[PDB]
Image: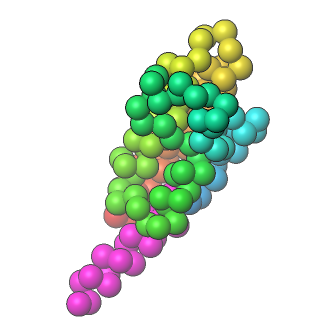
Amino acid sequence: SMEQVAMELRLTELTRLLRSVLDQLQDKDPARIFAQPVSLKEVPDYLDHIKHPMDFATMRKRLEAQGYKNLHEFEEDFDLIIDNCMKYNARDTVFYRAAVRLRDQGGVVLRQARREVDSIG
């Protein structure tokens, strides 16, 4: 139908905007701490601690399959990256501290993303 096509164009445009959001958030991680999944070879107990691992490469896979229906779903995944790290790692670690900085800097980007998503529909 024409409606299904219009819906699909909306999703494609959301995907375009979320790709730009993702790039901007990932720039706030210049150390690449959150770039890839925590390695289960190197941290073999990880899944005993963290039930829903997340990272930027995994988000990018989902994004490119158009697997984010709305900004809330995308934000959920970003918050998993941060919250997983702040639980597994102690406060006095470079990992924890990187997550705090990513959360703080990402907030700005996500605030305007939400306005754009609402504004453009």
Q: Write down the quadrant of residue 68 in the picture.
A: bottom left
Q: Write down the quadrant of residue 106 in the picture.
A: top right
Q: Is residue 118 above or below residue 88?
A: below
Answer yes or no: is residue 17 visible.
no
| Residue in the image at 50% along x and 19% along y | 87
In the image, residue 10 lies in the stretch drawn in magenta: yes
In the image, residue 13 lies in the stretch drawn in magenta: yes
Q: In the displayed structure, does residue 37 sit left or right of residue 4?
A: right
How many numbered marks does the figure carry? 0
Residue farthest toward the bottom in the current orientation of the protein: 1
Q: As rendered, which of 55 and 109 lies closer to the eye?
A: 55
In the rendered image, residue 7, in percent from the top left (x then y), is placed at 30, 76
Q: Quadrant of the C terminus?
A: bottom left
Q: As rendered, which of 35 and 14 lies closer to the eye?
A: 35
Q: Is residue 67 above or below residue 22?
A: below
Q: Which colour scheme appears in the figure?
A: rainbow
In the rendered image, residue 13, in percent from the top left (x then y), is placed at 45, 70
Q: Is residue 119 above or below residue 102?
A: below
In the rendered image, residue 86, in percent from the top left (x then y), is placed at 53, 21
Q: Quadrant of the N terminus?
A: bottom left
In the rendered image, residue 61, in percent from the top left (x then y), is placed at 53, 59
| Residue in the image at 67% along x and 31% along y | 42
Residue farthest toward the top in the current orientation of the protein: 92
Q: As rendered, which of 60 and 8 lies closer to the eye?
A: 60
Q: Which residues are magenta?
A: 1-18
Q: In the displayed structure, does residue 120 sit left or right of residue 97?
A: left
| Residue in the image at 53% along x and 27% along y | 46
Q: Is residue 41 above or below residue 10?
A: above
Answer yes or no: is residue 8 visible.
yes
Q: Main secondary structure of the magenta part?
A: helix
| Residue in the image at 45% along x and 24% along y | 48
